[PDB]
Amino acid sequence: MPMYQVKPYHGGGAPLRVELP
Amino acid sequence: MPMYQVKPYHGGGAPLRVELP
Amino acid sequence: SEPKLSKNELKRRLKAEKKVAEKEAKQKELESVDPNQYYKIRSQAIHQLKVNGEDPYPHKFHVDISLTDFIQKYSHLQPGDHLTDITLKVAGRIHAKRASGGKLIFYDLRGEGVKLQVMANSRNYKSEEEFIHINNKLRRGDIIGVQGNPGKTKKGELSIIPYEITLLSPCLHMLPHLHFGLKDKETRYRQRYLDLILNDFVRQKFIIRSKIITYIRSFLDELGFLEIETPMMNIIPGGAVAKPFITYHNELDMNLYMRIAPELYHKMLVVGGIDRVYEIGRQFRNEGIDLTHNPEFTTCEFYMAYADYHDLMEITEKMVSGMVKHITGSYKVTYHPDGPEGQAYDVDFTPPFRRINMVEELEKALGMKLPETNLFETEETRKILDDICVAKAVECPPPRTTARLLDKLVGEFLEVTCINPTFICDHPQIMSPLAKWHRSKEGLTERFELFVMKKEICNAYTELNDPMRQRQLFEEQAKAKAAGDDEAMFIDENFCTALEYGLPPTAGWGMGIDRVAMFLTDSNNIKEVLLFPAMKPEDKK
Amino acid sequence: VDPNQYYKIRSQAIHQLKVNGEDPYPHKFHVDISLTDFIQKYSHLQPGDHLTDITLKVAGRIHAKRASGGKLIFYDLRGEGVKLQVMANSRNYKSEEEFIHINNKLRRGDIIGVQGNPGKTKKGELSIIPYEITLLSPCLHMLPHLHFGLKDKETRYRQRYLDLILNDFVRQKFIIRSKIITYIRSFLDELGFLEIETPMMNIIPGGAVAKPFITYHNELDMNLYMRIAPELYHKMLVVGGIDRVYEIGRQFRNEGIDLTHNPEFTTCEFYMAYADYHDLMEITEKMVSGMVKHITGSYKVTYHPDGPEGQAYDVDFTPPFRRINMVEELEKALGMKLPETNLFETEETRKILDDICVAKAVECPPPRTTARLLDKLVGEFLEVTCINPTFICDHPQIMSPLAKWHRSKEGLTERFELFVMKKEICNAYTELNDPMRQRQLFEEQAKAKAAGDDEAMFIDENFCTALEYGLPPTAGWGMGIDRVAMFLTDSNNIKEVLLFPAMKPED
RNA sequence: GCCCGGAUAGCUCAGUCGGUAGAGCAUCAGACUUUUAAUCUGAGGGUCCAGGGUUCAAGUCCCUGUUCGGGCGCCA
Ligand SMILES: Nc1ncnc2c1ncn2[C@@H]1O[C@H](COP(=O)(O)O)[C@@H](O)[C@H]1O
Ligand SMILES: Nc1ncnc2c1ncn2[C@@H]1O[C@H](COP(=O)(O)O)[C@@H](O)[C@H]1O
Ligand SMILES: N[C@@H](CCCC[NH3+])C(=O)O
Ligand SMILES: N[C@@H](CCCC[NH3+])C(=O)O
Ligand SMILES: [Mg+2]
Ligand SMILES: [Mg+2]
Ligand code: NA
Ligand code: NA
């Protein structure tokens, strides 16, 4: 029953390291 | 000049390590 | 004007006359604005500040540290301490002004949900005359910026001893005292800013709602769901029973209909080749307003290809249990449906929810044997259902169709027992279109509804991917809705074409954000989680 | 052949399948692995091996049905943007009569599930040799020709599902748009902001200069205007006490529909307390440059304003963005000196601007007010040289009725606009917290609305009353997230970055 | 749509059997250099939701609205 795994589009493990000014 | 630091409301330490199906 | 005016007007006039006569006969028996007109006095003081160079609206104030960080950093000071070598700049709104002397005043800067004292002593101020000037300017409710050193009073109260206080934004209205606060529902809903200023739980409620929405997005994205933005208006009214919000477009010289549900566009996207999609957004239904219904409301809807409602029944369990544990810190919550003085219910959100089949549980409760699942469409079932509804003292307004009678019976019997989150599955096909038929039991569909505290929060079913049956149901809907005219505008002919092009076996799910917010904030009114509920304007003169 | 004949024949065939107990719409097919994972995990196979010990189930849409005899048929499965080959052979298939039966009912465009063993052909192509193929959902319409895929813009925009099926770059465009929105949300969340939701139906429209949509509420006999900007509610929330707020939402405009404007569009508006436009000017630099670097992979992008056959413009998104002043640069471009900024709300300045517009052949339909003339002059002279991102700041207060007055220069406001590829993407200013000046500005707008200039902002008593309760020094910022997607996805059309763009009805 | 209620000072609330609406807070003026809901002294205020009526007199009674809290519906 666990659905097949698709990989997250918006990267993962915090891919975007937003540069807080 | 950078604005004073405000802690993120949504944990801020990657708390959303969701347990997925 | 009006001859002899009205007895009222006449009456009103005399009292006045009597009022002014008594007033003059009293005060003179022995211009200053009356003290209750705080707005006029404050406005004139601010204007006088403007004209003589002391503009009370500075463009920029440089804040060094937030109040929460100040409290966290300097809570370790002993009473009587004064860190003369540390200078910090904070800002906030004045909530109290205790004048213990001509040269010692105490302010209560409230901001970010916390409070910080400000003990202004002219001895520590830069000079006496500017101390007097600034403390004469300041009033309660004014946004001010304080530069000073951390310290702790002899009592043991953390405070900032100011070297210079600047007025950032004066308040021109009376600010209610926090001991009484704001408790009028109409006043709280009309002026939400005052509600946030005076009440602290409102800010926590909205933080909780934001946390709810963030969690869902994160979970779905990790699963691999893509976020989409579907149109909010359409040129087609659609076949839904819910009344839409009509609108006019002058350039197209036509009417545009507000979105009721994004289901069709999501299914078209799944046809396109995007297996998993989701969208959190507003839906507009021109219907009634009560404690759990709003005409415009936020919902999260996702579609997952190569899935059925059985997989969704586990995904929903994981979503809800994880969200409740993440936000409230545990699995059990307390809900007050009637208010803080009514009965409190303990709602347990352990992972494995309860699952009940509608027909069997209804037979167990109603007490008798309803017909077989294939015979619901017969008028005999409608008749026996009407007999049961009448006998069991259940009231259903006309029309007394099988679907409406069954829904009334379900609400009366199967729904007073749904305190803990519960799945109600396998609806009859009549009560629900757009759901694939049940693969095993004839006459039933493949949907489920999640009910928490006797209220529906989730709704999911296997999507019907058969173009012929979907077209038949759409045409039946359009026939019922049109009552003449032409069904041309009550049938989506692009969704049908997409279905003919081919839709994989899909499962669709949809949750009401507002209702979840009310359940996780102990609010019995949907307006408590809406920032600005719609309030008709109060006629004024 | 005739698409109508193909549709009729396929409908008849599928009906025959239904009546024969061979249901072409199964309720569930358990997919074990995704196509992308299948490609990634078994790409190490040698050209010709056959892993008979592994049996996986995949699903997807058939894109090509090539025949190589009665015992070998190749299928081209397409899933998440990748390609897989299914070499159906009679030997490996569960049964011969069943191989023939399944090969006579499957055609291109059908959604099928394949259970089989991974392997590779002699030509070195990864494939899944099937043990059993299941038809999940037939395609009753004839898909467009392989060499003549969807190229008509109108057809692509009206039928987005066909565009997704045939064209692969559309999925990448929408993935990039989702990435943009997610990056903005993550940036603002980590900064300390709180996401909010403001009403989409307002008794009085306000917050921007636009023509609103009018709807009728049923429970409330009063009519309701659709949202044009959430500004007046964000400021009320900041008055309430929440210092940093933001909202990514849909705004509605009752203007014309073209290749750059849509009735409903997505914008992001954040509001900071104890800030000014000089701080937002740094935050915008940081976030825009970071988003470009995180999505494109570099700071330099290439944009084609008139299609791939036109000129290519290299836009650099180095964090520091160029900064210019409206009045000074407009004077330099015009080769003259405009009247003093403290005399901009008068009539002789309007006459001078009208004469300059006439001399410079700048076109401006009536009413020819000072604000509109200045906007036309700036668009014709200032924004046509802002290829790289650039800040145009210090606007006159006639062009901004909600921005705070400049500290040192009279008649100007504390605002800036971000212009990239000669188009505005951002708009930010220090909020006006003075109730009296705000009331005066609102009053002036009403004067105009009264006589022409219907676009003039409406009057709101509730916002002024809230301002009377004390609004801290705040700064507001708003970005239109449709143009950012157009520039990042290299599309000179809003309809390209919209899932279902509004289109003129066809006869 | 129908039904049952509410509306009194900026905020939180009294007001009898119709006889001049009044408490705390807030606001205004003045004291008091360690107070936290500071305290102490003195002062003013409301078309009692708005309109009409009955009455010698209406917050108080009758009748219209207005705006709201609920309950039915409506959202298949
Ligand atoms: N009028 C409404 N106001 C608020 N929430 C609603 C409303 N109607 C439905 N919902 C919620 O939204 C979810 C999905 O909407 P629906 O597609 O109507 O089932 C439901 O399960 C409800 O929790
Ligand atoms: N009709 C429209 N369609 C799409 N975007 C629009 C439309 N009108 C304004 N915008 C966006 O809003 C900004 C310009 O208007 P404004 O929001 O008032 O500054 C730009 O970011 C535009 O992309
Ligand atoms: N609007 C739908 C969305 C979830 C089911 C998807 N077909 C509902 O809540 O019933
Ligand atoms: N709401 C404005 C931008 C906000 C700027 C700061 N209040 C607009 O759409 O043009
Ligand atoms: Mg009433
Ligand atoms: Mg005093
Ligand atoms: Na009151
Ligand atoms: Na009194």
Image (cartoon, coloured by chain):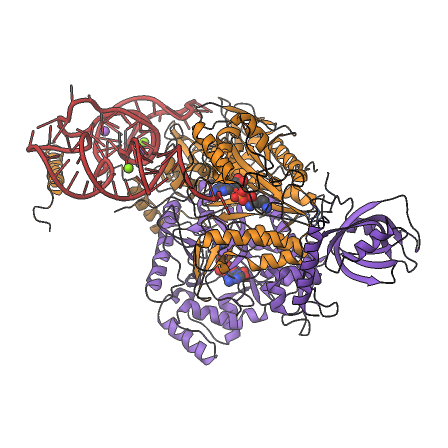
Chain colours: A blue, B brown, C orange, D purple, E red
Compared across the picture, whether D210 is left or right of B7 comes to left
Up-down: is C524 above or below C487? above
**The quarter of the displayed image where residue D316 is located:** bottom right
Q: Position of residue D56 (x, y in %)?
A: 82, 45
Question: What residue is at 49 percent from the left and 54 percent from the top?
Answer: C479
Q: Nearer the viewer, residue D35 or A1?
A: A1
Spot the residue most to the front: C380
Q: Nearer the viewer, residue D67 or D155?
A: D67
Q: Position of residue D162 (x, y in %)?
A: 66, 61
Residue C93 shows in this picture: yes
Compared across the picture, whether D472 is left or right of D76 comes to left
- In this figure, what is the number of numbered marks? 0
Up-down: is C14 above or below E15? below
Q: Nearer the viewer, residue A1 or D95?
A: D95
Residue C31 shows in this picture: no
Q: Position of residue C303 (x, y in %)?
A: 63, 47
Q: Position of residue D212 (x, y in %)?
A: 43, 59
Compared across the picture, whether D339 is left or right of E54 comes to right
Q: Nearer the viewer, residue C44 or D11?
A: D11
